[PDB]
Amino acid sequence: RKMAFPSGKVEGCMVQVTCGTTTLNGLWLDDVVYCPRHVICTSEDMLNPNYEDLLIRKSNHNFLVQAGNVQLRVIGHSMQNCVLKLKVDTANPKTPKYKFVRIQPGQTFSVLACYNGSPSGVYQCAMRPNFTIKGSGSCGSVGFNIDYDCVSFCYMHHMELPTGVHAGTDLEGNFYGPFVDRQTAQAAGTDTTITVNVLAWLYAAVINGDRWFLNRFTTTLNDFNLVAMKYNYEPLTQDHVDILGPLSAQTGIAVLDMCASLKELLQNGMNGRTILGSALLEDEFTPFDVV
Amino acid sequence: FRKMAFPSGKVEGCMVQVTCGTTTLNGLWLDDVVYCPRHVICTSEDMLNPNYEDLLIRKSNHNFLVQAGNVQLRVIGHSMQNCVLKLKVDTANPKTPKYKFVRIQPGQTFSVLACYNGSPSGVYQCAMRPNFTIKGSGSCGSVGFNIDYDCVSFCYMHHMELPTGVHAGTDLEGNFYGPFVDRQTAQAAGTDTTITVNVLAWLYAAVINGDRWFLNRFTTTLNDFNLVAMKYNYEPLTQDHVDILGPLSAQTGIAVLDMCASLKELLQNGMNGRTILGSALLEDEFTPFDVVRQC
């Protein structure tokens, strides 16, 4: 069961930002509301937005920020990459311990999906290798991990792409992948399985006592990558084999032996079986998640 | 289309740790009462055949250490309602949400906040299986809930792990779901069925999301589909069910019975190398309300 983190510490930060005709979600941390800069655009302006120019025509009072029933007073505003930063007259009393992290493809986090500043649901997801999220007016929703009462914020939703997938940035406002906050013809590159996440998950099934998919073979890293890429799997790298090291030594299965198992699995299928609870190979669990 | 849990911060503010003797598990703290599974007072020995009436007669308040994180709560009274043990406490939880104690039917879904000894670890969406079990994740005493307009409707509290890896528990008034007891005795889940009405709502969710390949010009019968359904271990489809799907049929232009034809024709021939919304197994853990609520 993919669990998302408890959302409460992020609910306490979700606000509503409005600029003219446009509303979306912002993130209240101390005395700064963070949100996507395109809150300042019309639909028209999304074709070719000049963000410096649009922002220069704005005062603090053009930005209406409501945390629940209470309108917050914006006393300054500043663009950093594609994120807007509104200084407010009131540090958020509900501010958790928190840090900003940029995550890399394959890693997981929870998303607090909101609508106009009210949290609507939480879900667990992975950053796909093409830098998108297969997910679910949630602009400004944030993705995060919690580690011993400290929320590490890693993602903010910005755009929806033509194939029904989401693109966004870190909280320094820097996009993941080649995407811009422009309604252009940008499209997701070919998406591939997070191979290392399937192997960590295969080791999880050995931990919960299911060994039926194993075989007597082994493989080389190179021969594995050659087979697996023909099924559109991400290359496995020496650094992936290392990260899996602790799962290996715990189940006594060496990594390349599990690689051999996966190769056969892609060749055969499940033959009716399920492994953990699933009838397909799951790539949204990391080696850190399983342990 | 992702399964989504309700946000859990209103429930997080309610989780406490409850220890009696050497036993430790999770409690729910609403106003001046802490709720938790009664088998907290149980010894490894008594768990084979316990007389909860007796072993709680012999317990008094000081036997229950209740900690709200970095705060021990003073128990000032105890009582049992069915299989839930209720603890009056010195203080009343200021984070208590507006709430209702509710009991749900098989095939309804809800969100669980798993906790390890009073500290919430994570949250997932799940469904109450037709055999009254939860396929799920030191979680004992964790609760299930649905949120509607800032009202937490609690519907589940976890008691038992069953030998097949599933979970068994009660409503918040202490009544078990399914033929299970809170003793360490041989108990198993019945053969599980698929939640038909939830599979049909999930097929509707697919035509809304633009995957319409499984549709067929055909119409079938309540009776003749139900025979095709008993043979695949699916729950029978009733008229209240069809009524429940009328919204989604109106929105999509596909009558429930014509969607049933689609379902019956995919139960025999499969997807022939296609998939529904990126999945090849028939998801049965989304209710109608869940699909409407998300579309």
Image (spheres, coloured by chain):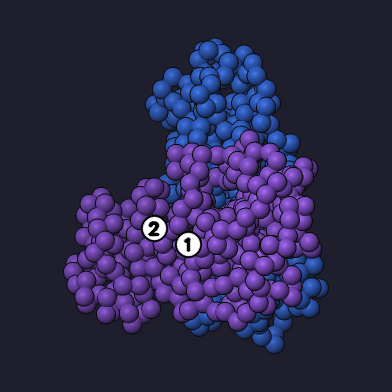
Chain colours: A blue, B purple
Residue beneath disc 1? B127
Q: Residue A129 carries which label?
A: none
- At horizontal 73% and vertical 56% (from top left) the residue drawn is B60
Pick the residue in front: A61 or A119. Answer: A119
Q: Can residue B167 be seen in this view?
A: yes
Left or right: residue B26 compared with residue B104 = right
Pick the residue in front: B227 or B54. Answer: B54
Q: Which mark is residue B287?
A: 2
**Label 2 SS:** loop
Locate residue A194, reporting x and y percent: 62, 61
Residue type, numbered disc 2: Thr
Among numbered discs 2 and 1, the one appearing first in the sequence = 1
Res. A247 image quadrant: bottom right
Locate residue B39, reporting x and y percent: 66, 65
Q: In this view, does A72 lie above or below B140?
A: above
- At horizontal 40% and vertical 53% (from top left) the residue drawn is B290
Res. B7 image quadrant: top right
